[PDB]
Length: 138
Ligand SMILES: C[C@@H](O[C@H]1O[C@H](CO)[C@@H](O)[C@H](O)[C@@H]1O)[C@H](N)C(=O)O
Ligand SMILES: [Cl-]
Ligand SMILES: [Cl-]
Image (cartoon, rainbow, N blue to C red; front, top):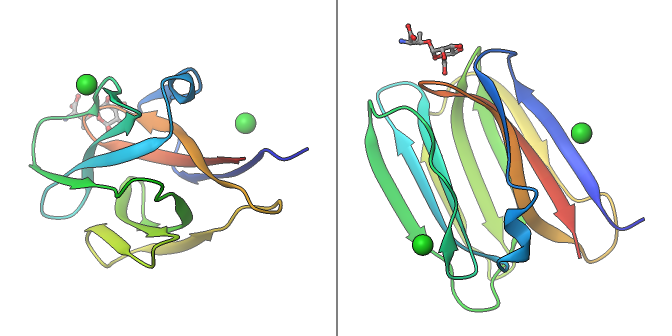
C-alpha cells in the first residue's frame, strides 16, 4: 500500500468534495487559493493542463501560484478553527507556498509511505473552506 490520507482538518460544515478522479488528468501543476481577512474562501487545483472545478465562496482575493515542471508537493501544513484559515505547500524544490492567516489550530501533514507525493485533495466546502484532506501516492 503506497497511498495514504492526512485529515480531515477542519469542522463538519458545508458539503463534501473530492478530487479523486482529477488525478487522471495529470500531476498537480498549479494552485489557486481565495483568501479574505481571516479564512480561506476557495480552492482550485490544476491537474496536468486541466483546472479542477472551483470549490468555496466568492468573498475574497484569488492567489495563484504555478509549479515548476517535475515539482511536487511533499508536505502540507496549515491552521483552522471552524473553517480553514492557513495553508502552506512544501515542494521538493524547496519552496514554501503560503496562503492565508497565521492563526488557529495547527496541523502538519506528511506522507506515510516511501517516496510518495501529494496527488489530490479533498474536504468540505460551502461559502468558505470548512475542511481539507490531503491524499498521498506515488
Ligand atoms: C455562513 C455561510 O454558510 C455557508 O458556508 C459555510 C462555510 O463554508 C458552511 O459551513 C455552511 O454549510 C454554508 O454552506 C453563508 N454566509 C450562508 O449563510 O449561507
Ligand atoms: Cl477517507
Ligand atoms: Cl483548465
